[PDB]
């Protein structure tokens, strides 16, 4: 219930800091990180025997209401 | 597939005297009505198994046609031979 005891993160308990300053009047921030993980298959056996990692495809989107300036 | 490979290997290897004195292969293309006498082409029996479809074999065959199977061998045809070919 209270901030000092809740177990979960919420929109009201987080601040988004860019270059040392807090972002004002954002609406959502969402981040996708995909490793391009792929399994290694084989003749004679139908199932893959390990996964391996290709490219660190890492992204964050910021959506914000336009401050009158700044 | 292994039986096929072993038949083709045995047919190919025994032909080391220029040409087998017996038959060529016989190819019963039953699906559309047609019949041929055929010999292994110089492409041969190419066998492969890629990553895609791991548990399925694939085979590639190429063949050259000697003649229709309706017709008997050229040299074996019984000529007229009337009179006497072996005069005394």
Image (cartoon, coloured by chain):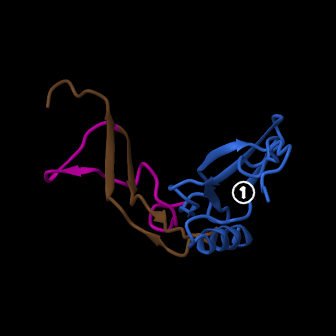
Task: Tell me what hue chain B is rendered in.
Answer: blue
State left or right for residue B76 relative to residue B14. right
Q: Residue at x 58, y 61 (%)?
A: B45
State left or right for residue A63 relative to residue A1. left
Category of crowding for the residue at label 1, using alpha-carbon neighbours closer than 10 angstroms: few (below 14), some (14–19), many (at least 20): some
Q: Is residue A2 magenta?
A: yes
Which image quarter is the C terminus of chain B in?
bottom right
Q: Position of residue A6 (x, y in %)?
A: 51, 64
Front-most of A58 and B35? B35
Q: Residue at x 60, y 70 (%)?
A: B15
Q: Is residue B35 magenta?
A: no
Q: Position of residue B25 (x, y in %)?
A: 72, 57
* Residues shaded magenta: A1-26
* In the image, residue B30 above or below residue A9: above
Q: Position of residue B82 (x, y in %)?
A: 86, 43
Determine the main secondary structure of the stretch shown in magenta: loop
Q: Quadrant of residue B2?
A: bottom right
Which image quarter is the N terminus of chain B in?
bottom right
Q: Quadrant of residue B32?
A: top right
Q: Which residue occupies the extreme front position in the image?
A: B88
Q: Position of residue A32 (x, y in %)?
A: 39, 51
Residue labelled with disc 1: B25
Front-most of B86 and A22? B86
Front-most of A14 and B29? B29
Q: Residue at x 45, y 67 (%)?
A: A4
Count numbered badges in the picture: 1
Q: Chain of mark 1?
A: B
- Helix, strand or loop at label 1? It is strand
- Which chain is drawn using brown? A
Front-most of B65 and B9? B65
* In the image, residue B8 above or below residue A17: below
């Amino acid at each position: 219930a209270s901030e000092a005891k809740q177990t979960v993160h919420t929109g009201n308990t987080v601040l988004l800091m860019i270059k040392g300053k807090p972002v004002g009047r954002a609406q959502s921030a969402s981040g996708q990180r995909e490793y391009g993980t792929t399994g290694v298959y084989e003749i004679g056996s139908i199932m893959p025997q390990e996964h391996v990692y290709l490219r660190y495809e890492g992204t964050i989107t910021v959506e914000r209401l336009r401050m009158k300036k700044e | 597939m292994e039986e096929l490979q072993s038949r083709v290997s045995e047919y190919a290897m025994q032909g080391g005297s220029g040409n087998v004195s017996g038959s060529y292969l016989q190819f019963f293309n039953f699906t559309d009505d047609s019949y041929y006498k055929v010999h292994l082409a110089p492409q041969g029996l190419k066998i492969t198994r890629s990553k895609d479809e791991p548990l399925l074999f694939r085979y590639e065959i190429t063949l050259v046609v000697i003649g229709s199977l309706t017709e008997a061998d050229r040299s074996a045809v019984t000529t007229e031979e009337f009179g006497n070919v072996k005069p005394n």
